[PDB]
Image (cartoon, coloured by chain):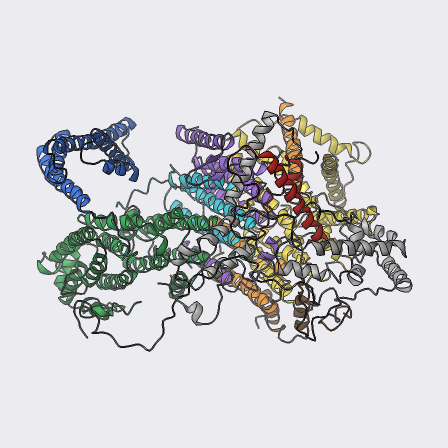
Amino acid sequence: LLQAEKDRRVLQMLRENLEEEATIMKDVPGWKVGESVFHTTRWVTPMMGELYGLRTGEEILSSTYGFIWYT
Amino acid sequence: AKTLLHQYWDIPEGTECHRKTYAATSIGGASGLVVSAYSVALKTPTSFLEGVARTGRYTFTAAAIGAIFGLTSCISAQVREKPDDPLNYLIGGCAGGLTLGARTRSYGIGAAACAYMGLTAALVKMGQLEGWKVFAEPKV
Amino acid sequence: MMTYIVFILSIIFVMGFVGFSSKPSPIYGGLGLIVSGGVGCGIVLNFGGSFLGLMVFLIYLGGMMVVFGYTTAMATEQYPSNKVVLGTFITGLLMEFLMVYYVLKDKEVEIVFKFNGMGDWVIYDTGDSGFFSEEAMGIAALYSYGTWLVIVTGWSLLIGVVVIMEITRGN
Amino acid sequence: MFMINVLTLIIPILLAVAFLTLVERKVLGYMQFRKGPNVVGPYGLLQPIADAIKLFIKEPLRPATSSISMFILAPILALTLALTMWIPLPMPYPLINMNLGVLFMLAMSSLAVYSILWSGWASNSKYALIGALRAVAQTISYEVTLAIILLSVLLMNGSFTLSTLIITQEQVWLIFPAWPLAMMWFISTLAETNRAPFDLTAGPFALFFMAEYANIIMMNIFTTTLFLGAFHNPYMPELYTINFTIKSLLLSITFLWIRASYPRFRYDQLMHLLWKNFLPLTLALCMWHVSLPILLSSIPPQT
Amino acid sequence: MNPIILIIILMTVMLGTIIVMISTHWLLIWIGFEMNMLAIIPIMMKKHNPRATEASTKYFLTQSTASMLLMMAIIINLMFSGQWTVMKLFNPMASMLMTMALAMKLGMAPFHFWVPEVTQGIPLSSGLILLTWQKLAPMSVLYQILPSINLDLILTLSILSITIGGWGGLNQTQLRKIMAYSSIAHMGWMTAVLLYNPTMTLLNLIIYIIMTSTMFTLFMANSTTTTLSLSHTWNKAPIMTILVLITLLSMGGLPPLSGFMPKWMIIQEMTKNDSIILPTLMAITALLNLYFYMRLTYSTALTMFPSTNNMKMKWQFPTTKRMTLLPTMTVLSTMLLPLTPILSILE
Amino acid sequence: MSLVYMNIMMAFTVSLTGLLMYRSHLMSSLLCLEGMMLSLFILATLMILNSHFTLASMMPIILLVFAACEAALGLSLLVMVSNTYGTDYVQNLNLLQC
Amino acid sequence: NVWAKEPVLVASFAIAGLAVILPTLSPYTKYSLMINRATPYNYPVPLRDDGNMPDVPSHPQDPQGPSLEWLKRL
Amino acid sequence: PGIVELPSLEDLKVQEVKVSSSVLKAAAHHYGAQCDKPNKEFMLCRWEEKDPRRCLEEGKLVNQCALEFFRQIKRHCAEPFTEYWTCIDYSGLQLFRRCRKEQAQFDKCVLDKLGWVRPDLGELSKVTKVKTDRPLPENPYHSRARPEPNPEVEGDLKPARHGSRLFFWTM
Amino acid sequence: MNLMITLLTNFTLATLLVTIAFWLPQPFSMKFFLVAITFLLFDLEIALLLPLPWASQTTNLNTMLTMALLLIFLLAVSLAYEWTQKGLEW
Amino acid sequence: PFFDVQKKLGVDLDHWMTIQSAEQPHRIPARCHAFEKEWIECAHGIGSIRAEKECKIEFEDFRECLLRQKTMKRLNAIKRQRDKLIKEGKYTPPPHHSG
């Protein structure tokens, strides 16, 4: 159950974050909207900057660095 | 380094002149700084003004040999109008050896330096003319 | 007090390495290596770091600098700063200031690399089911799989013991 | 609220240390045939208040230093160890629950060795340097022993969290499955606190004094958690805190009580005795406490 | 010194070198190099003169910084594509640091400043064992990691080590410094052909080890430091003289003798590539480092220096040194000329 | 590229230059060797943690214990040199000339 | 004999030798290894259903799979 | 190069079981008993394809199964299930040996009134078959073909051709 | 950074105690060295020993017992060697 | 030389400290497990030269799994672009927590 909620949440951040990118980068030349840099047609695990990117500090610090120095 | 020796050999020789002499002075300054760096590492001059003087002397002499080599290279290539011989750089190496002996102010060293630097410069241009690779194939 | 605390503790770390690479008296050198080891412990505990960074602390800041300060106390005197020491400290601070300034106000700084310049909340785990703090079970190997490694390590330390007593007048 | 937690830990340490000074003076007085200090008020609590504020009042040692910064840098390190070493100690709920705390204990003991060595170098001429050098030697020779013994007593419990220790002490005391190992550990605590029967024969004397007695209370609290005690039913921590305080007080009185009546050892007898008698015996107890949990089908639930 | 302790230290030298030979993990190679250092330190300072103490200090400092720079190269290798397999590396920078580490490990031209100083103030047994195993231990590693090295590194260190072991070498009558400069020149030779056919490198390693064992065994047969002591060995015994003749000429490498066979095969499988001027330069310098061999032979067995009595006294005692194994190594080292197709015994 | 690796490599060059240029005492050279050791330790440990290179996570502690006993041998050699001389300078070692 | 000479050494050798020997005569070591094996860290991964195999039970209540029963009974 | 194929926001709307942690931890075993039979479909999907954004229908299935199970335990006995999980909640990390008598009470409620025998140890283990409807995938590591085989050298060996074929020492 | 807050408060309060205590009133032996290196080498062997209570839950128990006894046995051989061979005598 | 007693005695005592994806003491993967398995299967029966010139694509995929260089470059470019357009002021950003 935790696994299913986790998968839906990370795909939710993927969908919303690529929507944000598609809104934000229509000035630069080139730039396909959602290319993986990789070549194989496989779901790679994202890198915590694809998930928690441009969230402005608070949630990314409480998410990445939470357990590391939480007690 | 590979970039400035490539800049020296990229010039057709040929006449595209005084860039040859500038590149040869850069070679001389680099080699003088190398040998002077070893010497100031292995002498402890005391004082440091003597160390700067020795490094300046080494860089100045090696740059002078490079400059005179490039000058008579350019002049012999323009005059003879035959850019394929090594005899012009034989003249070059002997002129560089003579001015090495001039800047150390003894003449037998200048004569032996004329002979050996002329032979090495003729061999360098001759090996560039036929084509002998740097240090390796490294294949079989 | 913010996100780039790993980067800032790394700044203090390289400052400590400069602070005893300027060649002071070796008890100041031992002080500099103790401060550097403490902030290196801070860096690796920021990566977490649950066991290994507290493990180095007993060995270097628990067993090695003790004997380095001991041998500073018993062998050399250095009984009375200098131009060369503090001048090299100034030039080391200048080089660090220049490198971190070019990290800050530009894209990337390249010795011969491409160091992608921003603070590292990336990369990290995406909240996995760790449950055993993977360092812990990793080092909780070496006794099932580790046949050869711990044998040659202990054998090397035994030979170190007989070497030390021989040079210090075996038998 | 967290800084309130820190201040409620490090405000009663001055109370504890000064009242430990009056308690050790009174208890030595009654091991001897002496009453007092009791002229300074009723039984003399204002007597530690008074001599503490007197030593603050009294004019400091004139320098006579070498690297003033280093000379201040040693006792500041000693007292900040004495403050930062009650963080993971569980009386029922510790300040910081850690993955591992006992290696932090041994590491901060080695930092106390740093304090001794730095004060010894920065102190004075060569004779005090030789004396402090022997002191650093006789301090460092026991962190082999205490870490070895602490490892062998936690090996019955497998984990380093120390709340697993306060769980696993519920049925029997840990003095019963390891009495000689605990006894040698207690002797090693007498070594680490650097008191009689072990010899040590400065500035600021009050700060070095403070580091000494906070080290003693630290080792006593860690002993009382480590080897004995009782259960802890939740939503009532006063019960375990009472039983913990009473057992730690009885053990500290026993500690000063063992101090009260024994002469100091010869130094080469001290090193000789430690190496040639505690070190093979610690190895024997370690190898038997390794090979025994694989015997008796009881390897701990290291989660 | 106890003989049990010396057997233990020899066991640990052999253990460290066999760990360097046999392992596939990088940590184990570093452990083998370090354990080789730790064991080889008390073979030196076998006496208690301060000469061996300063020599061991210099050796320990250079050896330890070489070991740690090697560890730097390995941690760079795992900063890039990371696995602990002794294979092709994954960085020109890491391979550069690693080959400079091994060049510090075994006698190379920028790094040779510790070799005559470590050999001068030590006895002969320590010098023999350090030359043999400290020139055997990195060659296995270089033989492993050859396919990812910039060639200019190896070739520059080889050329410059051959010409430094040549030119430095005309000035010393300290026989340990002579043998050390010979070691530098031959290690330049044995490193030069690493990227073309390493069978030649390992065969040259075998021949050099057997030659140096013969030479140091001849010096251990009668304790000498200078050439004048060798002239006294001429007076006291004649067969040592013809052995010095044959072994110095086989260090010289002449085609009737077996020391020529490693040069000639190098020139063959070097000139099957487009490298010709580099072989003739290397073999001119191989003509150069024969001159101190030749003046040594002139000092020992062919001209004769004036002698001192009490050699009259030493006539009444026949020789009573034990040799470890001198004659077998000698005729294995010098009459090996018609056995050139024992080249292919190696790979 | 996990930016901190640049700073720890620059710290390695700091400790390496401190190991190479050293004026008076051998103890400072040996302590900068120890600092270089700590640099390799920290750098490799952050790499293995972020890799989840969980099988062979032995490298930090075993690199540590080996180069620590190297530093022990260096301490004994420095004690021997300081025992047969007055001090432990880089000078008063100019005997045995190359 | 040496019991009067160096007694703590002899006691150390005795407890050392029994610590060496005593796992050979031991009726509990197989119990130790069964306890240590029967504790899972990772997920017990399922498999593609059947080649009509009389193993790999479908309900976790089904005792056809290998379970633990000496745990509850000491 | 290639772009990902993310699912839409139409599949990312399941009625999420926004319950807390201690009640979910205490309600685990009988949830393993009655439900958690059709989620090994999800587990086998996750371990035959390493690709969520694909197995999400079975994630919606386990989500609705857990919500249906908590609905069924919500409607009937017990309401002192609330008392049981709040007895186990404030006890630090939730040891299950803490509130044992009320565990027996909840078991007696659910047994005498509904059924659902508690899974004895160790029956939340013991590798279990599962059949699905989808056929099992092939090569989820999306790679190319194995490029070249080495021709294996075999055949009985001839002797040497005219000896060493070096300069001389023929035969 | 929570224990860094505790460390900061203890360090600042200690510096307040010291500075308010200060503004207000106004050769060698080899035997010294052998014990320290013996400490160092046995402490490193302690560092090799001490992950033993981490390790005791695996499916290879007899091998763990054997190599753990080998580590303490090697440590005991080193101890007994410097014991018998006048390493710590006076 | 490199010898092969490691293979000869049949005791594979040193092949387990070697790569990832050898069996950890609890069966957990690393971060780049499958990339390693496909790369090792790409370059197994290979003479380490067509490994250099044929398995390049999957090797670059594995390297960019291991370090994540250019993915961080893309994310950093997104961050710098986001900073300069919020410096401009167009669409005071609804990419954080709300519209």
Colour cyan belongs to chain:
F
- Whether residue D242 is situated above or below residue E244 in the rendered picture: above
> In the rendered view of the protein, which quadrant contains the N terminus of chain D?
top right
Instruction: Name the residue nearer the viewer: C43 or E92.
Output: E92
Residue C125 place in picture, x, y as percent: 61, 48
Chain D tint in image: yellow
Q: Is there any visible trace of residue C7 in the rendered image? A: no
Left or right, F50 with reference to G40:
left
Left or right, E16 with reference to C104:
left
Chain C tint in image: purple
Colour brown belongs to chain:
G
Determine which quarter of the picture holds residue A1: bottom right
Colour green belongs to chain:
E
Chain I tint in image: orange
Determine which quarter of the picture holds residue A64: top right
Chain A tint in image: red
> In the rendered view of the protein, which quadrant contains the C terminus of chain D?
bottom right
Residue D121 place in picture, x, y as percent: 51, 37
Colour blue belongs to chain:
B
Instruction: Name the residue nearer the viewer: F43 or A46.
Output: A46
Q: Is there any visible trace of residue E274 in the rendered image? A: yes
Left or right, H39 with reference to E131:
right
Residue G14 place in picture, x, y as percent: 60, 70
- Whether residue J77 is situated above or below residue E220 in the rendered picture: above
- Whether residue B6 is situated above or below residue G13 in the rendered picture: above
